[PDB]
Image (tube, rainbow, N blue to C red):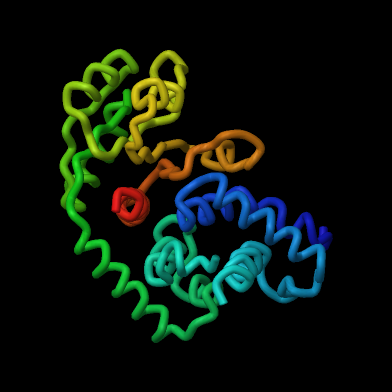
Length: 244
């Protein structure tokens, strides 16, 4: 109940999502989460005893790896927007996580909003069979300034549409009509093509165990524009730095 592991274990799945979103890969993101657990073993008292379990876990993760530091991979401004838009913390929770005053944290969100607005708009292909979901994500992507080149509903459509339209980013549901894997479909479609993919699921924790190959970016349905905006922004940032 008070057991230190039981306070931390339920929050590791979502912490890997934050780690993957900040590092750019499962291998790098999951590695930081494991290193955090090793750090806690060396000195168990580094965990905050009066914080809420989830806030203490994220605070510790940022405390160990951000004063290769996290800021070298994703600037703190964009980390601040990730904590709100993806990890679901409020402004004070995230400020406590990043150990900052409200004035310094609000300045980070504005800088993050500036950096994203300077990003070049991309062409997005959506793989989604449910119309209400495809309608929603298509409207959100275009509202953020990006272009939706097509919506594939089945794997067969997606193979045709991908080679026909050659998108620069893919938003794909993990499950399709016949319970077929959207993850397998994207993998078969891309082959060695290095195209950023963001997967949509109602249960992201199932792909955040760290026990097997898992996606880097997970949009949670029900989603909201901030979540999609941040994850698209991060996918484009890592792709740009890799190409340059």
